[PDB]
Amino acid sequence: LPERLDDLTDRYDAIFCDVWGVVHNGETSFAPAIAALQRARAKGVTIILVTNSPRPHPGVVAQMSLLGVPENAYDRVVTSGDVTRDLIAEGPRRIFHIGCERELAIYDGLDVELVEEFEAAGVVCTGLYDDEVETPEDYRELLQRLRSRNLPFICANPDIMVERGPRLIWCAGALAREYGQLGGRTLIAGKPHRPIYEAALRAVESIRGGSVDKSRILGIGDGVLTDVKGAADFGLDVLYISGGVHAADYAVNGDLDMAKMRPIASLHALV
Ligand code: NA
Image (cartoon, rainbow, N blue to C red):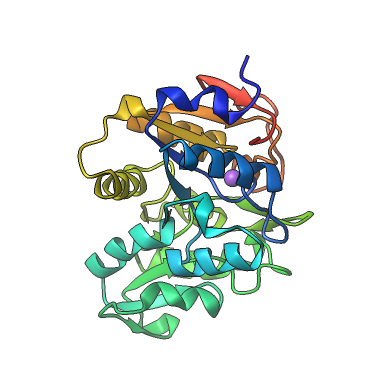
């Protein structure tokens, strides 16, 4: 039975570690998790933080710093926003944005034009317009209109919900799930899908100076349908954080299925 991360790291050269619910909750950071990651890096383990945030990595880094995460706890951050930019560049350039103002950072440097709904040829969803007060039901009519126009829907964050301190907040994935249920086409690159894992692997291989075999990479997370499924499908061992909120595993009705959860190891919290 593993008591702490240190009981596993002799067998791995790198870690792909979840952020929300494991390192911080959007309002405070978790000192034991930070310390465990620091100790792993001190023993030569490369740490990639891999998160479904729709923001590009520099915004996630800045937010972590504001929450007290020291830069010596990780080597690099790879986000769903980072890899979603490749989908955005590939799709139609006249885009209807669904998400908040800060999430417009995902378009920086891309050859795209943000347009009104009636003008759009594609949709990019980073989140809800005001995720502190809105729910997926508020989007039913809009999603129906977009689906009837056969617009492709890029989802920049596969999570259904995320924690924000004590609250649960709806994410872009909830709107993507509703769009798919209407019969609409969705395009997704974050966990559990392969593109974010390939980006994390490119990051490790560049940092370590050569190929890193999958048997030498440990995935860590609290989402069964994101972190666990994603690592397993990419061929990585996984450490499941069993005491997490599992916010990404909540359903669009706000229910969590307690039978959700094969991880090589389980830890109540990253310590
Ligand atoms: Na998480």
